[PDB]
Amino acid sequence: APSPEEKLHLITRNLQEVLGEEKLKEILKERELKIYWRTATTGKPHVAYFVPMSKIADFLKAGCEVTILFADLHAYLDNMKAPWELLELRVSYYENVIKAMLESIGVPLEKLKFIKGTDYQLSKEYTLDVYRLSSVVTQHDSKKAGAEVVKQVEHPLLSGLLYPGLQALDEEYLKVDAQFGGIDQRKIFTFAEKYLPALGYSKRVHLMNPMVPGLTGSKIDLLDRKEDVKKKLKKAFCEPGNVENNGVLSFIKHVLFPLKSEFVILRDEKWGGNKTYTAYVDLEKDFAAEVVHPGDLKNSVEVALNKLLDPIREKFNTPALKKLASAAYP
Amino acid sequence: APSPEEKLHLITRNLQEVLGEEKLKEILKERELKIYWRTATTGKPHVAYFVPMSKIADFLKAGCEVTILFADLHAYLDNMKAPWELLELRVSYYENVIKAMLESIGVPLEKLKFIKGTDYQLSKEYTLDVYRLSSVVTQHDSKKAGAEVVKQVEHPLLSGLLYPGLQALDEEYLKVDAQFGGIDQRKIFTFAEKYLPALGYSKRVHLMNPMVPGLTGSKIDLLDRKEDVKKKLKKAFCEPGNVENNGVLSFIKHVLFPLKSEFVILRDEKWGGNKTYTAYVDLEKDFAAEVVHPGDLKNSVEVALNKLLDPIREKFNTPALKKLASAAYP
């Protein structure tokens, strides 16, 4: 059972920024932290999705209650021509792939909750709060808050101005202590800290991951065959000695290293043989020194990534999920 | 029983503009017209309120179904410090004064319906439609539509951008054929004609009254004693021979003349004695010719207005309504 300090470390490791450390520590002295993470359901998740998922896994390992919101209302509003059933098929795909990813990482799911936006974002009390918020929030602040998150468009739509407030109110309605997301959500998060108190609701802790450079880029799909994973990785950019901007090193730092707090580099005996790193900074140092070659770095990632993907591919080859995957993406 | 032509005349007389004459005539060939009128519940109605009320009376006389929306949600949002019970007290005051006004005018109320905004404007289907609308309406169009109707303010609030869409959706949710209001609502009305079809809903007919100059202006309250009605009228501006901009003539044209399609001018025998006008243009002509003096015009209005107010004052002197009136305006 982790101490409050150990929980804090699991929760905050690899994050770019934490807002609300004071409250975060107060909570962890007494009880488990409750965390909300929002995901859109419009795309098709590729391996980059393991970056947020690795933090979700840390949260669960630390004993947190984690609520994942599947933003099905927004998915509908962003293309109302699409039928509610294909949209919900994609919601189901996301729910199942998230479960499979976390099972593969190896964390307890008892305190993981899935909720759909449509479950409550059209409810009476929530809607009244959306209106209350609209009566205190200036159009200027609404626009500013979504500047990095809302699609930049020809003539901006009214919906974009409403989105920051819905995401803030989610924190209250999901009854959480904190919201996690990427640092690109910072203005949405500061908006929530400013305006929730206007409605008599507490500001929340905010946990922000960095915007991590992609492993490749086509992209490696979560269900790509091992053959295609290999081929796509072979094409990945990875400059020798380059530690500042390196998608391969980033994937190790944020996804692979955290699994067991180690990473094995596969290397020919000629160049020193395999080495097991127990701190990421040690791997960074060797890569900068050019004694871990890009090809060996990529081979090491390929092996570990395929291990991570194996059980997911297995599960999605069952009749029910095989059908789901192809239907969700006809 | 009025013919379709007679109904059309009752419905459209004194209006500044009609949008949708084609559909209006089609409907009246077959059935009764259904009309929505919206009223805020934030002020305290004075005699100018008889201007819209006179059209409501015409609609009822013509056999129309009339739905009056009491905008209690907006009343709350415009001052959230105010308690829901004082707000609802004012709603009750408005409902009771409207009933008393129409009873005094003398029209059948069987097809008059009162509804509160909160009865449905927070409901699930309506809210989904608000979101759908926000996904097709540009921020630019939202702002433009409310330019004459939304309070011009320091830093404009998000709520102002939502208001035009709610008023459009009201037309669909109240299941009406037409919305009536002042010509200052024209941009809200054209917005509704443009955007309701985007959601698969029919555009409505729009009936627009002129912005009628006030009788005085303090203002004559609907419950002012006869003494104060007299005193306030004596102070009303009324330039001899001035027919273009004359609040006294406007009140005759829009409120008093329509009661029986006549108006009696009280005048000393010295100047020709009383005269009964059966067309407003005849009174206008005599006033322009300066053979109806401002003092006699005002005396004639005073007598007729006090007749209109008498039964209202009577009703509001009953214990229950006396209590309501003072509580609603503590």
Image (cartoon, coloured by chain):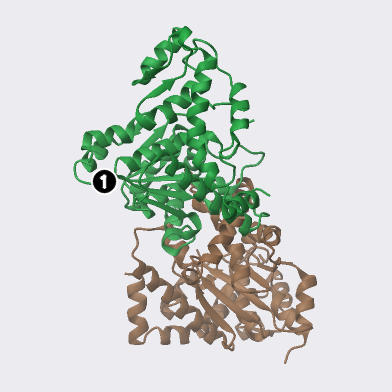
Chain colours: A green, B brown
Position of A266 relative to B250 (above/below):
above
User: Residue most toward the bottom?
Assistant: B1
Q: From the image, tell me which residue sits under label 1.
A: A32
Can residue B218 be seen in this snapshot? no
- Position of the C terminus of chain B, as image quadrant, is bottom left
x, y percentage for residue A70? 49, 50
Task: State which quadrant residue B19 falls in.
Answer: bottom right
The chain identifier of the residue carrying mark 1 reads: A
Position of B274 relative to A257 (above/below):
below
Position of B270 relative to A257 (above/below):
below
Q: Residue at x 36, y 72 (%)?
A: B328
x, y percentage for residue B251? 59, 73
Position of A180 relative to B309 (above/below):
above
Q: Residue at x 42, y 11 (%)?
A: A286
Q: Residue at x 41, y 79 (%)?
A: B225
- Image-based side of B94 in relation to B320, left or right: right
Front in this rendered view, residue A30 or A267: A267
Q: Residue at x 42, y 47 (%)?
A: A168
Tag 1's secondary structure? loop
x, y percentage for residue B249? 63, 71
